[PDB]
Length: 195
Length: 198
Ligand SMILES: NC(=O)c1ccc(OCc2cncs2)cc1
Image 1 (spheres, rainbow over the protein chains, first blue to last red):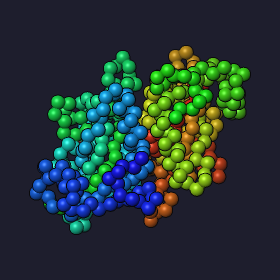
Image 2: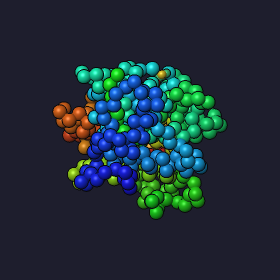
Image 3: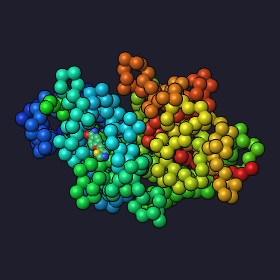
Image 4: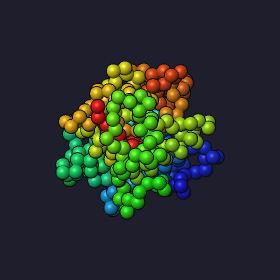
């Protein structure tokens, strides 16, 4: 059940689709970016259509929706990426096994594109082109992280296997989220931009 | 969606079911185990009914069954572990981020053995304070595999000029595989827990 707004893939399972500037989808994603990165120039925005990653992600979403016995498990966040990792992420998504890991050994996502836009996360390539994903993340129920976590903490130490879904730097006002499991993050758009 | 031979879980997502000796299900696992561990005695065999793990695993199997060319992508393998790890594995499966370094490393992933005798080593199935050893019997998506290397954090590419098109798993020896390493969540379903003693 591949989303309606995806465009036909001629029976293929992976496609990157360049969005048309000035149409609704492009304008929505651009506005999420320019909220904090209005000094940056957008060269292009690509929709990531990865059927297998989507399938695996949607399964985890339906599971977290049952487990948490409410919705609102999903946030739209940013991930800066070096050019050399874009093909792997487009195909395979985010892998904790591949910077500061102060809040645990998981994959990091920023609330603000400005954070992911730092050269440390979105390293300029030969031509000064920077790369950042807009990511559907299953943040679910979250707590403050700490160094050395390999999974989120338990919600209550009396049930050590019933875990928080993610961790953050700050629970009242989060600026980053860490997830510790494959298929808790779906890379939805890739933004190619310059300083 | 859940297999029809599973006991009714009411509306529950998790259950361990104690098997009865004389049942074909118990006897096939005991025989698989005793093939290489006839020195040990089985206390009990539990069927693991974990709906969420089962769902995510079956999705990965369907994807690998589509991607690969009529391959048998699944092997039934062994995994020894310590008592302290059993409640987490039962609920959340095998986490590569928790995995011990193997005496012979073919990569940084989760290790599964062809032979129960390998998993039965005290290094993997550590005797608990009561002298009970624990070994999972695990459906593993081995898929298309190659000989691993200690540096790996993901399976290697099949083709060095196509770095994102990966082997599904790695092994110690492609001619005579005795262990498999997987590097992704939901590539292994813990199906049975064997509790055993000397
Ligand atoms: N790739 C990214 O966009 C990215 C990477 C790392 C991020 O946080 C790392 C930190 C850990 N402790 C404090 S900062 C945020 C975003």
